[PDB]
Amino acid sequence: SAVTITLKTLQQQTFKIRMEPDETVKVLKEKIEAEKGRDAFPVAGQKLIYAGKILSDDVPIRDYRIDEKNFVVVMVTGSEYETMLTEIMSMGYERERVVAALRASYNNPHRAVEYLLTLEFLRDQPQFQNMRQVIQQNPALLPALLQQLGQENPQLLQQISRHQEQFIQMTPQEKEAIERLKALGFPESLVIQAYFACEKNENLAANFLLSQNF
């Protein structure tokens, strides 16, 4: 996953490097020190001229969108749980033992009685739930959280920045049977279509349309 980059030097000596279409130009600058050598190609005056201005060395070589067709003149100069406690405890178990099992047994009489004898990753997380449950009564929390809670998970921040819209959003023969039905009082799309009910007859489609609707 590569790309030959043509590098021209003010000395009128060009060549063709390749590196990767992403390597920070900082490494590309060093690439010129090894590509041409270090006899007179330092770094202090390393400016990658590609279009009048010199390309910096802190951005990826694929940030300027260079083209092999051109060379670069580089420079080098709570309760519901208790109501449940009685729902299960009543069987005979104790009280604290019931909630304990109701904490690891789906707080239900199912596993409890058993433990009583002896964009999507965030939309489902508790963080987003507070942003989609509290915002229902406070539109000011959306931004407050988007900068606090929503600004804590980089997994969504990388998308939400560009997905803020989705994040917030979350024939002349059959015509005779239609012209008549559409004229009898029935609609059109549901009539011209439903007509193909069973045998293109006037009841399979209508008969079932009059008994199911009227």
Image (cartoon, grey):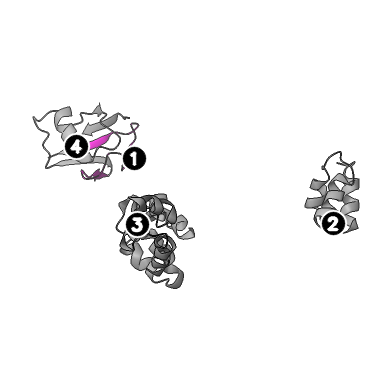
Q: Which residue is mark 3?
A: 103
If the image is split into quadrants, where does the N terminus sit?
Answer: top left
**Residue 75 x/y as whole percent:** 18, 39
Tell me how far mark 2 sits from mark 3, CA to CA.
Answer: 58 Å
User: Which range of residues does the magenta coloring cover?
Assistant: 53-73
- Choose the circle earlier in sequence order: 2 or 1: 1
Observer able to see residue 17: yes
Instruction: Give the answer, above or below, for where 75 lies relative to 156.
Output: above
Q: Nearer the viewer, mark 2 or mark 1?
A: 2
Callout 4–callout 2 Cβ contact below 8 Å: no
Residue 54 among magenta residues: yes
**Looking at the image, do the residues carrying marks 2 and 3 touch, with CB atoms under 8 Å apart?**
no
Neighbor class of circle 1 (other Cα within 10 Å; few <14, some 14-19, many 20+) is few
Residue at x-position 39% and y-position 67%: 82
Query: Where is residue 59 shown, x and y percent of the image?
Result: 25, 44
**Residue 65: which numbered mark, if any?**
1
Q: Quadrant of residue 122?
A: bottom left
Q: Number of marks in the image?
A: 4
Say what secondary structure mark 2 lies in. Answer: loop
Q: Is residue 150 visible?
A: no
Query: What residue is pinned by disc 4?
Result: 27
Q: Amino acid at mark 2?
A: Phe
